[PDB]
Image (cartoon, grey):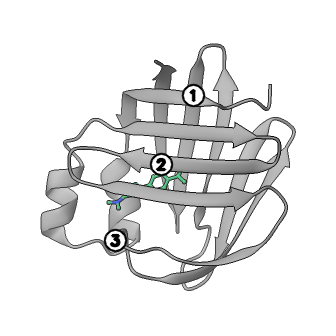
Amino acid sequence: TRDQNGTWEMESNENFEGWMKALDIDFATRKIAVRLTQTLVIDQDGDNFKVKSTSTFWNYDVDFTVGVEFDEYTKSLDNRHVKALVTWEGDVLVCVQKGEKENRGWKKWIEGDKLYEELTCGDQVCRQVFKKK
Ligand SMILES: *C/C=C(\C)c1ccc(-c2ccc(N(C)C)s2)cc1
């Protein structure tokens, strides 16, 4: 299924610190952030998405249309400019963020009642699993 609508509550988080380190996020932010449970809110209508990543420590929102490239500032994550594009590879939603960092982006897919996510940067991969609330 390509339907990722929902409020998604984290159940598993692996190598989140490695991904943050690959983005050069400062020590203090990384050490706090690695401890925290996350929520992902996805509002999807056709090709149009609004996505929110939240914890007690951050609230990062992005809107995009599948297949439409967009320039973005990564704001309170790492304050970089990238050229972003979200597409479907089968039923995997794939974001590539072109810019200073190689292999930068994310992937999301549904396995049952769960959303699986990869966050990638450089040679680091963070793997997460969320349950639908
Ligand atoms: C589909 C997933 C998206 C668009 C996403 C996931 C995770 C984040 C963030 C993780 C840490 C953040 N800070 C601001 C510390 S954001 C953003 C976007």
Q: Position of residue 45 (x, y in %)?
A: 76, 40
Specify the quadrant of the image occupied by residue 106.
Answer: bottom right
Q: Residue at x 55, y 85 (%)?
A: 100
Secondary structure beneath disc 2?
A: strand
Q: Does residue 79 appear left or right of residue 116 in this picture?
A: left
Q: Identify the amino acid type marked 3.
A: Ser
Mark 3: is the Cβ under 8 angstroms from ligand 1?
yes
Q: Identify the amino acid type marked 2.
A: Lys
User: Dot 1 corresponds to which residue?
Assistant: 6
Q: Residue at x 24, y 48 (%)?
A: 34
**Number of marks present in the image shown:** 3
Using the numbered discs, state the Cα–Cα distance from disc 1 to disc 2 in whole angstroms.
Answer: 11 Å
User: Dot 3 corresponds to which residue?
Assistant: 76
User: Dot 2 corresponds to which residue?
Assistant: 52
Q: Position of residue 48 (x, y in %)?
A: 75, 50
* Residue nearest the viewer, comparing 63 with 57: 63
Dot 3: within a 10 Å radius of its alpha carbon, few (fewer than 14), some, or many (20 or more) residues?
Answer: few
Q: Quadrant of ligand 1?
A: bottom left
Mark 2: is the Cβ under 8 angstroms from ligand 1?
no
Q: Identify the amino acid type marked 1.
A: Gly
Q: Residue at x 66, y 14 (%)?
A: 112
Q: Does residue 58 appear left or right of residue 119 in this picture?
A: left
Q: Earlier in the sequence, mark 1 or mark 2?
A: 1
